[PDB]
Image: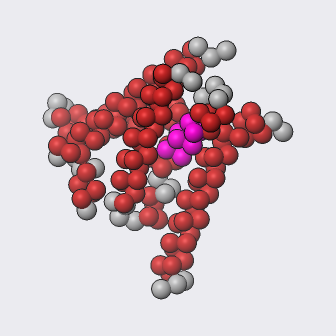
């Protein structure tokens, strides 16, 4: 079956998504069957939100660039540690938006949730297993969708 080649890396992402689905199902059951400052942190033109979104966007650019470099040179490293630090920042930001989620019914299933699901656990598995699996880090390029809003936050267009 070749589970180590492809299934091993995607297994972490699948298990994380399944755990999120279990959590959301438990939350729905509790809400139905059973008995912010962070919101300001991801605001728009505000300085804190502007800085946070710009940092996330530039880190996404750097992650895409290093992924392209790895793909070009494809047949530990300093770029691996840089990617690990950027993923740590990304997961901290993900938890920050988690504690600011107005409704968890659509937070765990949101597009950026899928992006981090297919980005970070694959990075963990690649680091632990010491393999050149690219994973789905290219999905970080989806974060480039924040380009116009940042400009709208910088008031250039």
Residue 48 vertical position relative to residue 32 in the rendered view, above or below: above
Q: Nearer the viewer, residue 152 or 92?
A: 92
Residue 138 vertical position relative to residue 71 in the rendered view, above or below: below
Residue shown at 44% from the left, 64% from the top = 104
Residue 21 highlighted magenta (yes or no): no
Query: Where residue 6 appears, x then y in whole percent?
Result: 72, 36
Q: Main secondary structure of the magenta part?
A: helix
Residue shown at 64% from the left, 50% from the top = 14
Q: Quadrant of residue 56?
A: top left
Query: Where residue 73 appears, x then y in whole percent?
Result: 58, 13
Q: Quadrant of the C terminus?
A: top left
Query: Where residue 71 appears, x then y in whole percent?
Result: 58, 19
Q: Is residue 45 something that shows in the picture? A: no
For the image, the number of numbered tags is: 0
Residue shown at 67% from the left, 15% from the top = 75
Residue shown at 45% from the left, 22% from the top = 65
Q: Is residue 41 something that shows in the picture? A: yes
| Magenta segment | 116-124
Q: Nearer the viewer, residue 19 or 141?
A: 19
Q: Quadrant of residue 49?
A: top left
Q: Quadrant of residue 155?
A: top left
């Amino acid at each position: 079956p070749g589970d180590r080649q492809w299934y091993s890396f995607l297994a972490s992402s699948l298990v994380t998504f399944g755990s999120g689905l279990v959590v959301i199902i438990i939350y729905r059951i509790v809400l139905w069957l059973c008995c912010d400052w962070a919101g300001e942190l991801i605001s728009g033109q505000t300085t804190t939100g502007r800085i946070l979104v710009g940092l996330v966007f530039l880190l996404s650019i750097a992650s895409l660039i290093i992924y392209f470099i790895d793909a070009s040179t494809n047949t530990s490293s300093t770029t691996q540690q840089v990617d690990l630090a950027f993923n740590v920042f990304f997961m901290i930001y993900f938890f920050i938006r988690f504690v600011a989620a107005n409704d968890k019914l659509w937070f765990w299933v949101e597009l950026f949730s899928f992006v981090d699901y297919f980005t970070i656990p694959p990075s963990f598995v690649a680091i632990y297993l010491d393999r050149n699996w690219l994973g789905l880090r290219f999905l970080r390029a989806l974060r480039l969708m924040s380009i116009p809003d940042i400009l709208t936050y910088l008031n250039v267009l």
